[PDB]
Amino acid sequence: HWGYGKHNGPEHWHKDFPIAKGERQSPVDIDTHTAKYDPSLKPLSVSYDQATSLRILNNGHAFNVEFDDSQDKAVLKGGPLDGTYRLIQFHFHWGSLDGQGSEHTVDKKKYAAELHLVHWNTKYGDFGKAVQQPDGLAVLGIFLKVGSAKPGLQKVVDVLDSIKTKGKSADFTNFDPRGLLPESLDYWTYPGSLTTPPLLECVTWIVLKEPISVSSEQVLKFRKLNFNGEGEPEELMVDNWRPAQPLKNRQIKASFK
Ligand SMILES: NS(=O)(=O)c1c(F)c(F)c(-n2cc(CC3CCCCC3)nn2)c(F)c1F
Ligand SMILES: [Zn+2]
Image 1 (tube, helix red, strand yellow):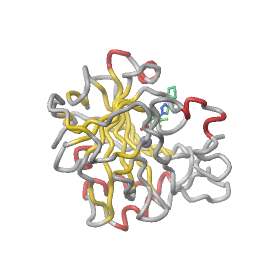
Image 2 (cartoon, protein in one colour):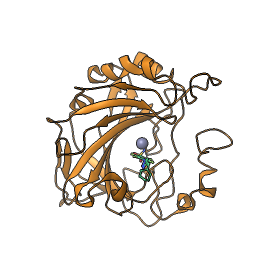
Image 3 (tube, protein in one colour):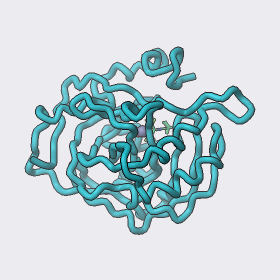
């Protein structure tokens, strides 16, 4: 099945998921000079004060921190969005080296990692219905650069030893995702897709301009995770990113000048 290796990686995905060559695939390069300020774009509304984290899971491609999305507890609204999108999970993509790892790029620059806070449009009732809709998901993307530690990330780092291999999960309650956000909510936005199979074209991407800084020790601990299951040959979970895809008939909009 699909993964990030030589023989099952992004260049192969189109054989099982032809939408890989579709008209609104993600990620993309964000050409900052070509993005257009849209003065009518509203500020983002990130309402995470009542967020209820439940569990962290190594799913063999990344780790997901999962939330209770059975009520409007942690929601994203405003910006380019109409309606209310509920936080279901967050996860990261990262590199084997500090100079690669992000999915989106900025003027072709790659960051060490990229955080995806995944939200679904409540008008569709559940996440599985939402992914079948062009406006089903809103994913808030945040770049990570290596420098100072991010204190709000440490609880995540601390638990990774307990979910080293594919299929392992751990309780992960009372985690506050507000601790993962940069100061500014200035963003770029465009219509795109899931960046892993099934690559569905259901995402409004909202990518923050300001990266967060994480320490070298923090990202080193991401790189100690495994793609494999327990008792299988060890394959370090690194370079779990899809490269930039063609922009095609899309314009990236900026919330800021
Ligand atoms: N990196 S990302 O764009 O933010 C990103 C995500 F946030 C995802 F949640 C998924 N994801 C995994 C499933 C399983 C089922 C696929 C279809 C039926 C319901 C769910 N669906 N969506 C995904 F593939 C992805 F690429
Ligand atoms: Zn992702």
